[PDB]
Amino acid sequence: SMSYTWTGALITPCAAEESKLPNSLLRHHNMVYATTSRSAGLRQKKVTFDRLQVLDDHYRDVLKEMKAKASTVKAKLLSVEEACKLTPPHSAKSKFGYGAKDVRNLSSKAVNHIHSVWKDLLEDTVTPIDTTIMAKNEVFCVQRKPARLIVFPDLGVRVCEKMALYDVVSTLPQVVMGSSYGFQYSPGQRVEFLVNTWKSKKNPMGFSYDTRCFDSTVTENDIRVEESIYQCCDLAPEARQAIKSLTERLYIGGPLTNSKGQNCGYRRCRASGVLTTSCGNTLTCYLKASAACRAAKLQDCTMLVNGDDLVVICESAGTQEDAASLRVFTEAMTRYSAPPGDPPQPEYDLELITSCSSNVSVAHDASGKRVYYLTRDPTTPLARAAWETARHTPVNSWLGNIIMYAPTLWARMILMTHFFSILLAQEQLEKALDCQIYGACYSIEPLDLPQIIERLHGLSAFSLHSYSPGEINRVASCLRKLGVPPLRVWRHRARSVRARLLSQGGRAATCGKYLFNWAVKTKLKLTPISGWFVAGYSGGDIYH
Ligand SMILES: Cc1ccc2oc(=O)ccc2c1
């Protein structure tokens, strides 16, 4: 059916959206923008299209295998307390007279509404449930993106989704998909898995596969198959019912309502802001892509899936032969309703593959041993840092990036330096901050960063040094592009920040010792001193 239909009501912003940047970080302010509701119409047109889906034996057989692993999962209901506790403090308020504070505080109004909504889910498995549609405000750098579309139900329901399904989405995928399930990995563990399966092959080939607006390609069938996979678990008979009702009344589609309460149309594909979105997309992508691998007769495949993001590493059959089987894989994905954005291409070098917006690169530790780490073109992370350093923002990409990308040349020399300089200057190293990891919101203390890095990465991450020239280029190149100081300058700024940090002692001294040991010249020798990378909750309204 049609992915979306539109009345003509506009997608309407709730508050004023600043499209541009209000300068110690980057001179070229004008290359940095935020998407707004102004660009909705374009995104609307890219994401709205009909879906033809043609299954086959290869799909049916994979689905049957998934279902048998799923059948060995036990999962439980969460109490309202447990589900209320998972809500982020600044989650959108309900239209029925209570917000997230009340949810978090177990106010008997919020609880009693939630009981009413849970009750309605069990009595009625048919009425589509309302959703709100919103343009996202996301920052990037020039060379332009239309705002992405978020779609989400009222708070009362979000809390019900938790009761019904939090344990399924936190436990099932890793059982069904084993090592393919990407969100069970920290960065370090992810590099290790990619690198080791690269070396496990006689003659390796790998490829990323970019699905054209994945959410829109997901059909109502896809979502019901998905439901049927959850039902394989040993579930409470009430949980079994709420899940049926949630998928029929919400996951499958429903009316779309703007900030003004006008009706915008009707969704028949994935909602990006429900609890199952991450688990759904991951299971759905793993299913089709596994099917696609069989159609293409790809030998000895390893997959790594993160929502709609896919990498495959396998045995080469030769260059002609690989390219040809890649096209088959693509025809097969396209039959299953998941056609390609960029055409997918074979790569014979692990470092040249991008997945979850990252590629492996190689460097050396203090002994001179070769160490692998994940990195990326740093344009967006710097862009959003420039923004977060400028306007005030409730979420901090920079800290997330520090954590995700601690070993990188760009995160060490630029981010840590910049933000520790700012916290230092505003006497604010102590304040916990909200950042996002695999879509869950964590409150994190910057002073704890050394411990966090040693655990997610290893002591090596404070001492890496002979970075690949390709990496080094992309970095200084990005910096020229954006108008940010060259790396020589950061080294000098870091030397100073290192020093002030040490002069404060305790944990700020530890930050000085460990984080900026790269900057010194003659190095201090460094000695040693979660429930975090377990599953994906993007769009899922989660707080740990
Ligand atoms: C390990 C790893 C790799 C890529 C990622 O991409 C993201 O957008 C968010 C988190 C993340 C984590």
Image (cartoon, rainbow, N blue to C red):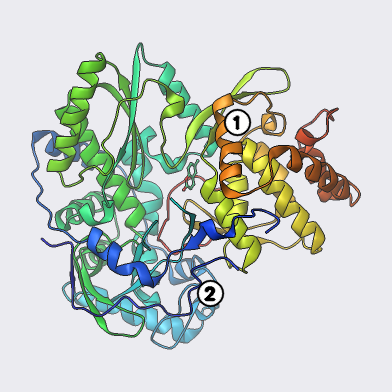
The location of residue 527, given as percent across then percent down, is 79, 31
Amino acid on which the number 2 mark rests in the picture: Arg
The location of residue 78, given as percent across then percent down, is 41, 63
Task: Left or right? Give the position of 448 relative to 293.
Answer: right
- Hey, which quadrant is residue 493 in on the image? top right
Q: In the displayed structure, would residue 236 be above or below residue 153?
A: above
The residue carrying pointer 2 sits among few (fewer than 14), some (14 to 19) or many (20 or more) residues within 10 Å by Cα, namely some
- Hey, which quadrant is residue 286 in on the image? top left
Q: Secondary structure at mark 1?
A: helix
Q: Please tell me which residue is depicted at 34% across the width and 13% down the height of the picture.
A: 203
Q: Which residue is mark 2?
A: 104
Q: Which residue is mark 1?
A: 472
Of the two numbered discs 1 and 2 in the rendering, the one whose residue sits closer to the viewer: 1
> Can you see residue 274?
no
Amino acid on which the number 1 mark rests in the picture: Ile
**Nearer to the camera, 259 or 45:** 45
Q: CA distance from mark 1 to mark 2?
A: 46 Å
Please count the marks in the image. Answer: 2
On the rendered image, what quadrant is the C terminus found in? bottom right
The location of residue 213, given as percent across then percent down, is 27, 52
Q: Is mark 1 within 8 Å of ligand 1?
A: no
Task: Left or right? Give the position of 530 relative to 360.
Answer: right
